Length: 278
Ligand code: NA
Image (cartoon, rainbow, N blue to C red):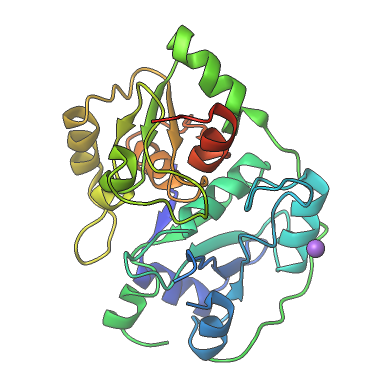
């Protein structure tokens, strides 16, 4: 329950606060090389917001980028960012779509045991149309954050591979149609486009309005039905590198289905390890 917060909710909760129930805004902007999320933050951001670096708060040994980090690493990261036991996290991003990389971080706090995490509707795109309540860097104090990762939130290469036979869960890919069909290139050097056999293409953009807001739960229910996805049966989301897949997990969450694991490795890992030849 209660996973998303509006542009007006956040304006009020700051001029609150409350006692034993703190707030902490986050700019989890992340882009494919095309924009500097940290420099853009320092130029323009929401008061109190600290920048959440998706590639920094990641597994330090993997050759893949923004793989879920270890429990001790996420505790040290979230802690130093102003997140504790009673903290209420609100994540946004300055993306053109409204929300893009923000649901990835929403999913991350949930996976490590901190369910007191919400998302800002429309992100910064709509924090512009609806008023203008900043510059600088940012300075929150620590933590004593505890992290216990629930592996039920993540699917591995082997799980996806073995599902090709078992069919125990539905797989939704949130990449653009072109990339999924194999008609548009992949943004990574040497990686070819295409998709995992038996997966459904539901691009992450289908979950949002042209305004950039999240579609209604009834609209998302209609989408899942039209794409031939049964929200009563198990569902796993995938994409290019495990970022926009969390939009699918969010869509299903707002429909009453919180158990939607993410294939963290996603297309880049699949292309590397399965080596599809066409
Ligand atoms: Na480091």
